[PDB]
Amino acid sequence: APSIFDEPLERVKNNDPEMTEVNVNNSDCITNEILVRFTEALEFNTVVKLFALANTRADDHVAFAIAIMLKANKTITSLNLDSNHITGKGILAIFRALLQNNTLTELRFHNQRHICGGKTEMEIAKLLKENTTLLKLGYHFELAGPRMTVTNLLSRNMDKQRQKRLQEQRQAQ
Ligand SMILES: [Cl-]
Ligand code: NA
Ligand code: NA
Ligand code: NA
Image (cartoon, rainbow, N blue to C red):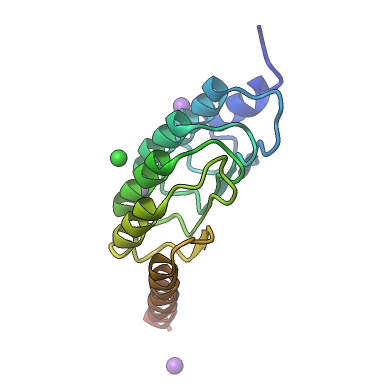
């Protein structure tokens, strides 16, 4: 029973050099199994820069798969998880994976079905301390402490990566 996602999934699996994004945002036809299949196909894909699956009913199982994938994938720079069913458990799995990923620069997960809660926000801020490459975090923190801490950490990271880009440019100047 071939779905409409067969071709894009197989392009990812083939490392199609023209398949530079996977954007399945708003796909009413997609399933959690297909989302996991895309996620596993991305582990060793070296082309895709964006994985966007906003508003696809993605749940914690999809987020766990994504966390695993982020430990392998060195190519995706932007990940859109907005408007799904992911809980603090899924979000924290991803921030734990970001302890072992230095290439993702944008993560967003606005408007989940349920807020993640203050305890999760605190642990997000703690985990982010250890990652110096995330530059954009699309989430509005309910608690001010995590909110301002994360804002300061993203600024830290932006400053650090600008320093590293100048250094790299100067290196062969
Ligand atoms: Cl975890
Ligand atoms: Na694969
Ligand atoms: Na990685
Ligand atoms: Na200078």
